Image 1 (tube, rainbow over the protein chains, first blue to last red):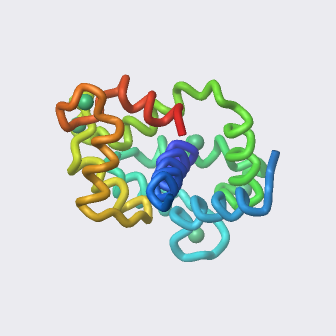
Image 2 (cartoon, rainbow over the protein chains, first blue to last red):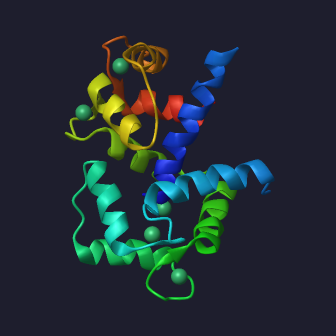
Length: 21
Length: 146
Ligand SMILES: [Ca+2]
Ligand SMILES: [Ca+2]
Ligand SMILES: [Ca+2]
Ligand SMILES: [Ca+2]
Ligand SMILES: [Cl-]
């Protein structure tokens, strides 16, 4: 689940940007 | 192709697993993380996951090995199965729906930080049918998008 956990981490990253604005 | 930043995001992921920072991910370490994610793999299953990435076969995964695999799966964006795997990590009770509680728990363990406000907004953005949960179809759209 190494890459799957990275995907989740990556989605949160994307979120914290679609938030930052 | 790889960049200085992407490498840091991967070192991020690697650190989650390499708890004692000895530079290697052991079978024991993988088990701890997997169990914190709601999975209960046997030692046999843990050995097999390590072996998939352990290119020089010394029994553990180092950063160069971790990077190799991560960069390769990334070059692949037809990883529908990788997305189901991420879904499974979230859906701890296996009912096919990711609840706000399930989402928060994984984020808190995956080294994240989410306020119940952010947890709700995360779901609300992906919750197409508005039932407050994120089903598989919704998860894909949420993950495959941006
Ligand atoms: Ca270690
Ligand atoms: Ca190795
Ligand atoms: Ca569930
Ligand atoms: Ca829904
Ligand atoms: Cl993987």
